[PDB]
Amino acid sequence: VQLVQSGAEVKKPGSSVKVSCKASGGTFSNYAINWVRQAPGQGLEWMGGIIPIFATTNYAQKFQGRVTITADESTSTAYMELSSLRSEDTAVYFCARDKHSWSYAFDIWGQGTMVTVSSASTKGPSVFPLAPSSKSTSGGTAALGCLVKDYFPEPVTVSWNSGALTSGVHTFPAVLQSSGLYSLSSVVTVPSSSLGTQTYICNVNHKPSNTKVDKKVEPKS
Amino acid sequence: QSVLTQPPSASGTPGLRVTISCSGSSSNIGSNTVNWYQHLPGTAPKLLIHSNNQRPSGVPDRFSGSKSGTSASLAISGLQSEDEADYYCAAWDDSLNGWVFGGGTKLTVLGQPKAAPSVTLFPPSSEELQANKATLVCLISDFYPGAVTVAWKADSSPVKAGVETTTPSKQSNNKYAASSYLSLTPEQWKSHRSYSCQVTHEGSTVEKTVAPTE
Image (cartoon, rainbow over all chains, first blue to last red; front, side, top):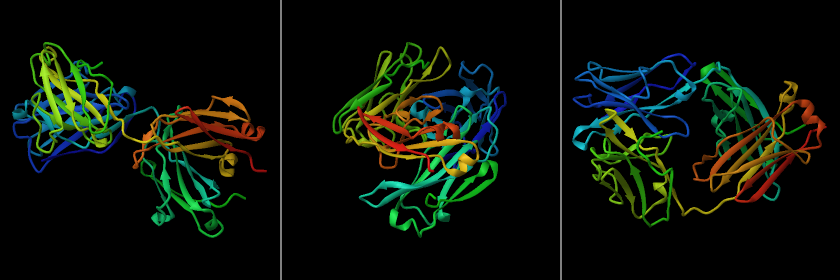
């Protein structure tokens, strides 16, 4: 038995979010489904639970009538709805099944659902070339890349030469700026001897804004 | 704050033992069983111990649990680098009528060799300058332990405004990466002879310098 959760959500403060959790290769039986979250740089926090066959729910006191947990026995899917969202609610939300014979331990967990709560609005990135510069003169190596600036929300994907270039590629985790927008860089380590002849194109995809950008990275001139 | 108290950090030597404590009260640990979870952010938590001291199938006998009074402990013997993770205790609380978790303990396994950061600094692109912005990009990789401090300079003068630096992130090779961005106006960029990014790691500094292209 596996637990499959719904995809990432991006919400504004004051809104409500509903995350699902579907039992795959099994049913809820007489077990409970619990919801546990983890905010960035914080520990696990229990939100509440439900025993679907008996319709009994239990909620964490710190969530004062903000959380609603439901389930439908027909499709073996449980739900967690969190209302009046605040920036502090940005977290990964997990569902887990308990096991009465194991003193109600959470033995099976879903993969987690990221919920981002922000006042920012969707924005496709501005992509800028980072012209080749010397990395190791003795090694005859250069670094070139692309700056993927000011986008929202995560994620973006970066490929080089439509995926034909993978060796020496390092795409760095994004910075979250005070502006509420993200920026990242992707750098390729290449031989300096190849610079006058080899083409380097970075391909940037930002599905949330339906943005696809290509950027040729040529030697500085 | 978590109702079960755990130390925020623990450290152990490869091949040796480490103990992680969990302190509670009469309504939780005092009356109920304790469960332990291992977690690496980016993956779901994994059940390690249930019913105070029982291992689920697939959990090595190196992990053991115990409970005494209002406290519980997780012991890890023959420590392996793969044990580096966060460890959480949990118990039902009769007074709250709900589950309570400890704050978690980050376990460090002391084996790993120290590695100096590799630093790449890029100046603003002509395209970005044409868009009336100027971003300097400092990329830091392959350092261990996972902590660095970044200092930026305009010629030789320190610059604190317009600096945004990421927290270090673990790479595939178990070393760490970070990046630092300095936002300037085209005027500020063109007004100095150069800018520098200085990365300090374990007291030692690695510096890169860039300058406008005339």
